[PDB]
Length: 237
Length: 249
Ligand SMILES: *S(=O)(=O)c1cccc(S(=O)(=O)Nc2cc(C3=CCCC3)ccc2C(=O)O)c1
Ligand SMILES: *S(=O)(=O)c1cccc(S(=O)(=O)Nc2cc(C3=CCCC3)ccc2C(=O)O)c1
Ligand SMILES: [Cl-]
Image 1 (cartoon, protein in one colour):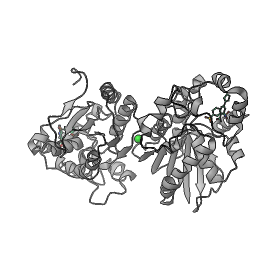
Image 2 (tube, rainbow over the protein chains, first blue to last red; image 1 turned 60 degrees about the vertical axis):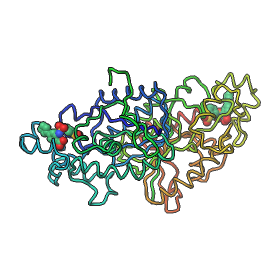
Image 3 (tube, rainbow over the protein chains, first blue to last red; image 1 turned 90 degrees about the vertical axis):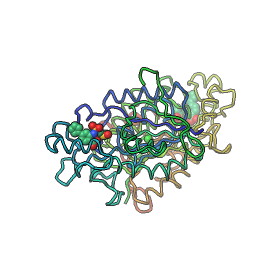
Image 4 (cartoon, protein in one colour; image 1 turned 120 degrees about the vertical axis):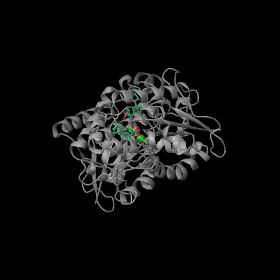
């Protein structure tokens, strides 16, 4: 069985402020860095070896990957970065905390966005405080005008993440390369939804743990042979 | 027409033991990490931007690159690693200090090796304590038997670094991508000798500072407009270049 490992990054600087990050490039907090260290040590203790790594273009995921590669002494591995593994774009909610979001948009709309698979948050418009910071960041300069989001539902995030899974990661797995993916909750949710054939309701009920190596065993058709498993001592899990 | 930046990593844990590292994967010391941070901050303060980065498969260079990318807020850049940018392979000298090398191999051979462009150190044989650690590391599993060195003169190092420059780096430069290369003294010497047309004698004497960004302005044919220039406070650079010139002497 092919072996695939996923890791979701840990706590970020804006988690501490209860602020929606999305495509804002928030760094890990010291605690999120420590989580990545512990996940890397769990991989080292289990003897895991990789051949290629994939991550987003967001530093909280990239730094998680760097920390893991340092812990497992595989800093020399090829690394591929792609915006398609980015966190969901939270649109006009970017940079707001919970209270500001409730005050600006109302409890009704908040519950809609919270529980909906396919209703996006408001768009990030040119007067938004983070519009230039994100939409004019040169790391997205090669995206076409229809690819750069102003906002994303979970459905949207999964829709632009899965082409990268299908067209780049799958061929690598099929040639026997041992893949590590360090990314974000919602983009990894896309991968999990696809691997396991989950419903919209099922994937919205799925919260992946942070900082914990998530291990899949895949058959010749890249179908999981059993549920995802977690690495680390039992209490940390 | 084009701008190119090189950075040589700083002190490693084995430098503090006065031991030959070569392809041994020694990590940075605190001082080596600090030099990377200062080079990154120099690039940040001058507003430098890159589009692609090249480094070796050795962590002292990779960690220097990581520290620079952190400092300049460009951790999202594509990074390409290659053994062809590795440090010179010191063969059987790997792991030895200067006294042990002199005792084992003689002052006569030491003098030859240190002054010579094309006489390699002794081969690292299977009984060498670091043979399995280096020659059987899976990161080199895809190298042909002819590509995997047992030892390298400076000429050998340059001969395997320049194919990567010509095949992988030059096309990125010609596309207009702003390239950063974070590597090692001897592989960077290959790039410098090629760009500036220096003699063997001059490239073996050339002072290559650690942790100081090295900047080239190149014309459309990739010829330097001026020789390498150094980024950073003038007095810090001046003192650093006096230091390396003194170490050469
Ligand atoms: S996202 O990165 O997965 C995310 C980040 C923070 C919170 C959530 S959520 O609570 O699961 N969903 C959500 C909540 C809210 C508000 C709650 C209290 C005031 C605003 C707004 C939007 C969302 C959402 O679109 O997911 C998810
Ligand atoms: S290498 O990393 O560039 C290097 C490191 C230390 C010293 C040199 S060298 O003096 O220029 N050349 C050299 C010296 C020696 C010894 C000196 C005293 C005892 C052994 C051995 C080999 C070399 C060499 O291969 O160039 C270079
Ligand atoms: Cl990297």
